Image (tube, rainbow, N blue to C red):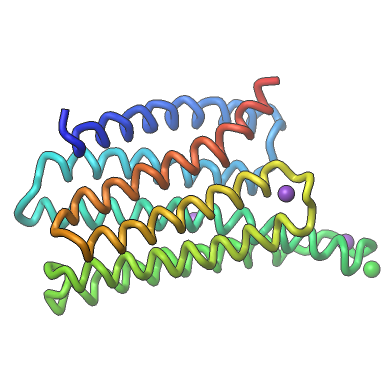
Length: 233
Ligand SMILES: [Cl-]
Ligand SMILES: [K+]
Ligand SMILES: [K+]
Ligand SMILES: [K+]
């Protein structure tokens, strides 16, 4: 099989895993076994991984035309969704952990989950606005438009890495923090390689698809799977 076909096979394996983890996490949440904020963010992350695998299949099937651009856009948006859900968890866990350090005697702050969610949702909205702007100018159909979208993803990956770093510095024994940090490192590395690949040749579809699969693999293996495994024990 060609490279793009191998990438779709891998993404479909990840989507299969994601559907199964969604079922396990839902039962765990109904049984009082997982925190609601973490559950809701992992659920969003898994749904982005399912969408990524769908867009990748469409990209393989539509190398040209409007369906090609729509598959590329859907694929990039699902990558943004995975990073924003990672950012949401790291930010929320950090804010809660910081309050414990600065003032352990204070009551639960209701603003913290709302603050983490609002910040992560802003990135999703900003990306949708950027896509619309490039689509209106026509720049979306040129290589410079795709670079601008990948540069946005790289900046989001850097912000996600910073959030994961701050969270991991609070508790070095926190395994979820360690998984978010390593995933954020791999995701940033994958996007920096994709930006390099897009300058070296015209294989733009392969560059983005490769980054997309690496991003979903990192999230599944390093962030989601260990939480699910702990619930199984
Ligand atoms: Cl206090
Ligand atoms: K407190
Ligand atoms: K959301
Ligand atoms: K940690």
